[PDB]
Amino acid sequence: SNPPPPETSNPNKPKRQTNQLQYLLRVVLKTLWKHQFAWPFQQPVDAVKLNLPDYYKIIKTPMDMGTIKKRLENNYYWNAQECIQDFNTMFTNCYIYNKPGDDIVLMAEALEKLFLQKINELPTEE
Ligand SMILES: CCCNS(=O)(=O)c1ccc([C@H]2CC(=O)N(C)C2)cc1
Image (cartoon, rainbow, N blue to C red; front, side):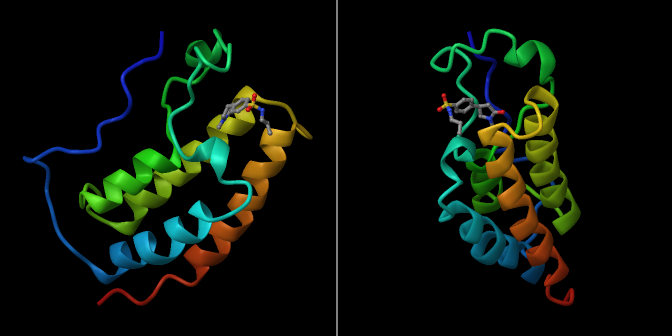
């Protein structure tokens, strides 16, 4: 079985709209979402379909871009750092589970470089 996917909605959570969060959805997420290497990261890892029975034994903090997208659409993040941390958990999860040179790792590394550049270009907090 798969675990429940991470929380993406929480009506009682602290909520605000900021120019850096708008940028993270409009620029960072969407730039990564259209990438030719995005598809394995666009939804939670399905350990049943992929026959990875050990995945959720090793990965205890799952994360993916589908969850990030929904968290941004739902204003779930209070600041850019909370969003950035989820991206970094997605990347590191992939490097922990897999091995250097694996196709899935090469894909994550392409996305990570783009992400890093987009965070360098974060607009000034307004
Ligand atoms: C380029 C490799 C494609 N092979 S695959 O059988 O479709 C496939 C295998 C494994 C995954 C998981 C593993 C992982 O760490 N993820 C973010 C996703 C996803 C897809």
